[PDB]
Image 1 (cartoon, rainbow over the protein chains, first blue to last red):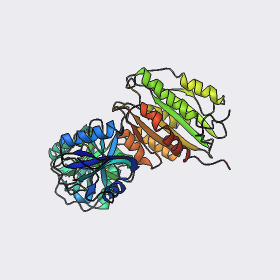
Image 2 (cartoon, one colour; image 1 turned 180 degrees about the vertical axis):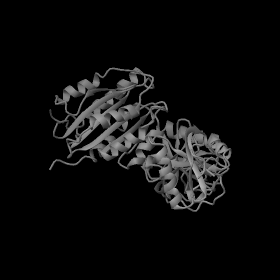
Image 3 (cartoon, each protein chain N blue to C red; image 1 turned 135 degrees about the vertical axis):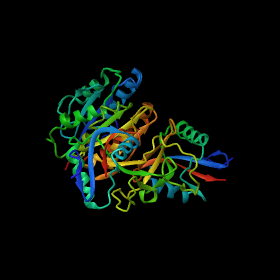
Image 4 (cartoon, rainbow over the protein chains, first blue to last red; image 1 turned 90 degrees about the vertical axis):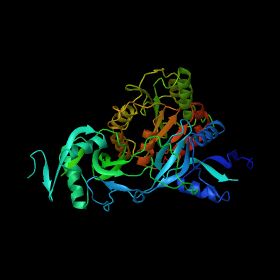
Length: 123
Length: 125
Length: 202
């Protein structure tokens, strides 16, 4: 299917890294690694379970960075009394996501904290 | 000014309730009192509700619901992935789309929280 | 007593081993855990002037087998660690143990030169009720400069609490292992990190 050390799954290739890097660096690492490569994105339940088995089985990894994050001034935050949120008493820091290879749940996690990850590219 | 059990300020009346309730319920009640969950505009009205919350919830072990939430149709709010993929499927263990005054910072910071987590709240009329 | 293995952290350090005592770990798994504590100790210059060691098995409450001021033979301590009785309780309150660590173990920083580290070996999740003051304790530690290294083991670890800890400071590097078997593996990567947080005897 794919190329050495990368596992193949439905037109895509995944490789788990134990190296433990930050979210923003892990993504940068997946890009300057493979042409059109990225930090793993889960578009189905079966794809997520494939990754977890890959990360848990051949590497016994529990947490991995996923290509999902955002800042609050990006979300549709609205009040209930009508006012328009301009006073951002919310940290500007971004939210990041890790996947757990046990149940496949996604958990918010501090971005600037090293975590093993998973890269993904399309053949 | 308002009801004795409440506190007036800038043409608005607030009050912190020790009794817990989901973000939903908390609002359904604020409305039942001709209002909504507190909303902050100025930094003035902010530290005010901070004191107001600080004075009432003297113990600091609970977060107080406010009137801010994430309208997002999705579990988490990121619409696109890093690879350009549209966020269709999700599996967030527990999405947090309802904000409340962060008690771990003395109610001065806002923290998103699980809507459904029974916390005390703040109403405004 | 001379250095058993080459890995021989010799810096000013006060390390506290907190061992999950819940039944989320079989008896055998607990032994593998206890074996971990011993291995680590075989890689530390356990002296009152270098690396002091403490071992605590927590469950409903906390039971200390070794304290930082226990001036015993380094071999005698590892022997104690290896013989740590198995509780198997239903709940292993991390809050209760971190409270203990903060209000008892490091109640007074009488060793200002050394670094304080709490290796929180956890394999379960305490009921949301005992977690009332969790953050307040973790914060208290941050003030006492007591680094807290959350080590998640098995599929029942808290993760939410682990994350909370790793969020207080970067020094609180977390480790999420698939099982106790991963203790043997990542044992060294842990001692290196643990060691690199301690000063250096001038």
